[PDB]
Image: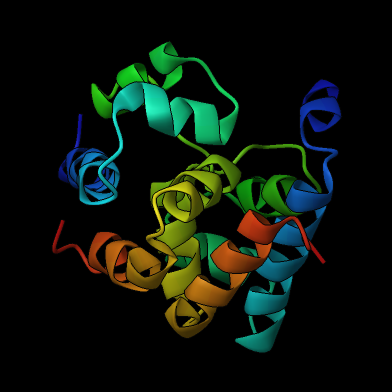
Length: 77
Length: 85
């Protein structure tokens, strides 16, 4: 449990919500079950980079990627 | 290397290429980069050769240590599109 991981999950959920996507809608876009989205957003499942890319693309958020990753890197998470 | 069987997709191979090229572009040896990440050299070697998985937070730190936060958007978009070069 860290600020960076807590901030990441916040941003992941907010990207989904900003796309007007239910957890089930996002899972369909990713070709994953609803449980995958659920567990990621509760921090039970850590994403790798590839999963991160796919999630943000599916949320139409590739434009906020740079800011999310910079914030994490810089300790401002 | 049991792990690299999980890390064989075009996207992993591309990501790894970009991780390595970021390091090499910053003029860092694997040791130099690991020191900046407070990691053993083996961490850097293993990530680059698809022997260890990288989470997003580890990616952020690696790219920042390589002064490559500017190419993060390109790396992630390329992975996303399945053009995974």
